[PDB]
Structures are given as C-alpha cells and as structure tokens.
Image (cartoon, rainbow over all chains, first blue to last red; front, side, top):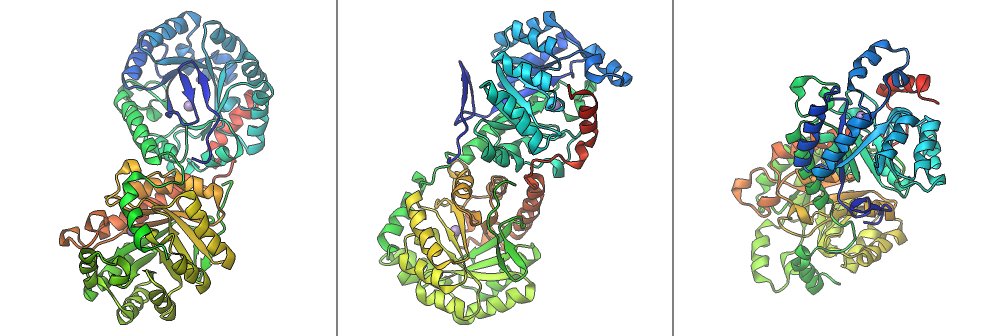
Length: 285
Length: 285
Ligand SMILES: [Mn+2]
Ligand SMILES: [Mn+2]
C-alpha cells in the first residue's frame, strides 16, 4: 500500500500496519449477568478464532441516570472485579484477549489493576472528557469509537490521547440501533485513514456480517461486532449480535478479503508475466 | 469524503467525483465477429442498465505479430468501420454508450471519425507510446488500464496525458486470465487514488462479480467487466465474462454498495439522533 498505519505492537498484540485485521467479539451485556454464560461466550469466541472478547464495566445509575427503565434493564448484567478476574483467566487459558469498556473512572482503575492492556471507550463517551483523560493517562492501549461525533468532536478526543502519546486506535461507528445499510457511511474509514496516522477500524451495529466485511474491503484494520452464543435467549442486544458460527465466518471472510486487497503496491503480479512478455515483445513502440 | 477525484463530464454522464460508479460491459471479442450477436449484446447490456458497452478495434496481424495461432483466433472477430457504425447506432437507440479499444492509430482515427467520445487503451499498450500520444492528442476521454505495469511505467503513461490536459481515467487491472482472487491487489485502487487526482477504477478479469463489487467497496469509481450473452457458446474470453443477468446484478449491487459507502463526511447520521441526545444530557462530564 501507499498508506500504512503506524502499527501498535504490545507483545503478541500487533494491530495496524500490515498486520491481520484485529477482530473483537463484543459480548457487551448479552450474558445478562450470568457468569457461566459469559465464560461460555469466551470459550466459543476463542473457538471461532476471534482475536479478542470485550465486556462492559459500568454502574447502571451512573450510566443512565434518571432513565429508570434502562437502569433496571442493565442492572442484572453488572460484573465486578471478582467476575472480570475469572473472565480474564478463562480468556488467557483459551488464548483470546480479554478487555472491557469502562464507563467511569472507578471501573477504568479496576480494569488497569487487574492487568488489562487495552481499554475500549464507547461512542457515547467521545465527549466524556474526564473519562478520556483518565484513559489517556493510564498508558494503556485505547480504542475509541466515534459514533455520534462530528469532525471537531473527534479531533478534540484524539488530541487528548496525542498529548499523552497513548497507543491509540479509532473505530468508525454509527450509533443507530439497528444500523441500516444506507447509514453505514463506510467511506468515513478512508476519510479517517487519510486524516490520521494511527490504525482505523470499524464497529458494527448491523444485523449481519456483510457490512463489517465491506468495511474491511473499505480499509478497516479492526472490526468490532456484537456477539451472542444464542440469539434465541433474547439477551441484551441480541438483534445486532452474531452467533459463534457467524463470528467464525466473519473471521475467515475477513482473512479472505484481506488477501484480495493484497499488498497495495504498484507492481505487477507474477501471474501477469506472460502478458508482460507479450507487451515487451510487440507493444513497445 | 476527504479526497474526491476531479470529475469528468461528457453530456449527461459524469465520471468520478461523487457521481455513480460508471459500469462498462466489455464485449471484447466474445461475439466472434457475428454482427447480429454483437447487436444482441448491446440490447441486453442496455436492458441490464450498464452505462456503456465496449468493443475492440484492431488489426490481427499488427496486434499479435508472428504468433500465427493468436492471429487466426482473433481474425474472425475483427470488425471494421461499417460494423462499428451499426453498433454505435444500435447503442444510441438503446440508450447505452458505445466505445471501443483501438489497438493502433488507424483504428483510433476511425473511432474518432465515427464520433466516439471515449477511448479505452488496453493494459498491454501502457508502454505503447505512439498509441498513448495519439490518444492524448485526440481530445477524447481516455480510459487506460494498468495491468502489467510498475509505478514508473504508470507515471510515464500518465505524464503523456497530463501534458495534453486530456480527460483521463486510470483503471487498476491484473493481466491474468482468469485472475485468481488472491492476485486482485484491490488496495492498489486506494494507492492510485492517493497518488493521482483523476478518477480511478477497476477492470476485472475474474470469474465472477464478487471481485468487482469488492473493488467498488475499496474505492473504484469505474468498473469494467467482460460480458457475454451466453458462456456456453464458448466465445473468446467466455470464462471471465458475465451473462446478462449477472451484469444486471453487478449494476444493482454496485449501487447498493455505493449507498453503504456513503458520503464519507465526518458527521453523524440522522438516525444517531437518540444517542446524541443521550450523550449530550448525561455523558458530557
Ligand atoms: Mn456497540
Ligand atoms: Mn480485459
């Protein structure tokens, strides 16, 4: 390629540059607070060969305030340090990366204390200056999604991490539920890749995997997709969540599209040598 | 978007910029020199809503030299001026644009004389300085494919058209028949869009429409696809040619993927309004 993002390398973490697309299974709140179900989600995400599985670390009242129905809905799905330690341990055993989205500073501090190496910051927090500054100060790798955000809002958020030289990844994202095809605006990925030097990816909220695969073809270097072991359980966000076989197809189809994208250099392929020989023998005149 | 190519206009059709993808059905030599078959090809390409149908204007001996097998294969498919006039008349009647690839200056002059407004130059002629200079001096829209070519060979050809200020379009292309998907190097499209200001597209030599559709997702603003009424006739290039229903699907799927790509601006979609209001009321802390 011409454009190559500055890769983020932390041990075996290798994101951007000419590395494989980093695929995140967003378990989110779909486990409903069932710890055994969350552990099962890790097992089956590792079997699907996702690179990482992501959870959410939040206080319901802090997150939703006076929306009593939202509070009651997400209250059962809260996990604390003891559960996140068990989930991190199962993830290490199954060779899949564990991390989570903190929604406040106490949860961020807890995630750093249990040894996570990556933080996700949700789209709704792209203007949460206190939380962004705490993420930048942590020194950890930060993935920020830009759903809801204008170009100026993105620049303000990006500057917070540039100022601390945080390893930083930005995901194009549309905070629409569910996200329709005509709202994907996947060419924003290239707009961001032209504007910034760090890796750009895509976080999906559609009802399938076609849009994230198209996002890979349009340049995404990271893919985040909501994830469930079984939509029939009707857990939180089930409608936009991929089941394990669909996650596995996302992984293998991403690899296939990456092969099709190729090296990006302006040079002939060896499969063209017969036409090169013909060109050189008769058409140079 | 961020970058936009400088659009090219000819009548009511505009190529590049934020115009629809321009779709070319390459009839090639697949008609085998059967004029009635070539006329049917125009009818069915227009019904499929391709923007243009393209033919090839060549002398077999000039094109293939002492390769007597190749000369005998393509000699029956030669059309002359009288045939191209009939093909152009049919295209206008059916509301599809007609043009052709000249392989020598006599055929280029003939095409301009009968009123064609676009010239295609084949990948094998990207080092054919005499032909490229005649195309650049013609004043017509020139579409060039860069199969076989290195960056420096592309730059040499581009410089010819920059000097004459020709309306110019470049197609990424891999001169392999049929082209394996792992050879497609579709990220070369973005490399070319970053290097050059004129519209960049893709000429396909694969066995399906998936690769050209991925090329749209990777930024192609023009798609050329080989075309046949019926692969079972085993005409020249049958294996890489789309049949009319498949051409029609390429057209409608290209429009769908363009809608998914969107405008490329860093501004939220209207459907994100609920999440914006949530963000502004509770998460600006
Ligand atoms: Mn999400
Ligand atoms: Mn061709």
